[PDB]
Image (tube, rainbow over all chains, first blue to last red; front, side, top):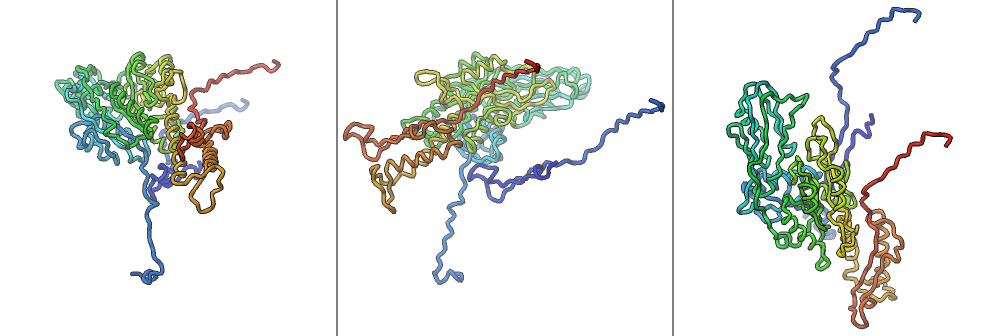
Length: 53
Length: 500
């Protein structure tokens, strides 16, 4: 949808309070869309027999 | 030595003084601990992480569970302090009897919401299982962290509170499987919940002055329903907010579970406590919700003191999960009566009959403060934001004024020469006004008149002639703090006509 807003990387400094976050710790949030299984295909056949309608 | 350092022309020092960690979120969780724990009672101890909770404060104790909720709530907090308490000498453990009758004739699932959603059990009952087998299965499925030791006896499950006192009197087992369309409860099996004995004598420590002498705590969480113990904590935090000695502020978080009359009677004019009004039919163990609320408030203090722990976004106790119901705990009449009398009301995030779990969120983030020392109904400390933010403002102004400590003070006409560590009341007031104007939109609102709102007087123009002492100043600051934001009365007026 938006790879820029789906994957975010923050340091531990911008997640934890002031002077509490530790250096070298990162927080990666990834909002991805995996393939789905595919459960049912509801097919609705509608035979058309008329030519002038 | 090492080349370029051996001749002593370059002398090198490392100075690792910048990179020291700040404390963090100073929340003191107080509650009873079981004798299985290794912690020393009546002593404030740092709790580093959720790992040592069971070892230190007992397995399934009240303090263990409240600390588990405090750790689930805040981000990665390690500055959680605990204050373990011993059970009263003559304390009586509450005993509930979950009696099961059968036998089951059809298969099914037996789901039970005991305590919180973390403790729920979900067993599979087959056809022909006697009540004994079902009780044994439920006991074997009861989580060990559940603050109730479960023993099966001929189909009756005796749940004995791990901690003596009245704190065990708030267990609500809900057979959240009846009438379910998805999970079909077995035919036969009948779950009944009775409480054969009540909790009794509670701890009344009253030793905060000694245990927490000057070790300040932004948030005190009390995991007891005893109003005497809550009153002792209230008196302590009130002393912490006292002009007499140097204030190092705090704010207490207690709950009051009962009927509307009982909850309102348990309240007083305590600006120091944020009383959490819980209905009699409250499913979650109350100290868990109280601990989540206090932990959220603390975890805000660390970041944004002006934030109000309120609403589905900022006051959402996502760790707590209670089953959804159409009966809304407090009716809106009771909600208005509680919010009127300075009580924090909490409600389900979603209402439904589908029987999911919902996280309670805080309706109003207020203290139990309604009226002044003249009883003069006042609004200074109505909000928990107000206490948190008055503390933050006092500390920020004090840390700013500390820069005038040590400086020699000249008269307000002297133009201090350069290189002289000195100042005069005029420069002091100018710097204070600049500080206050720097905190507009961060700590105050704007200033009606910053010149007439912030005044600095020497002790000579306050005291009588030749009575004032040199070097003593009186600073009056009339600021406007951010307000909480309680209600938005929206009045929709649809207009359908074009020629009117």
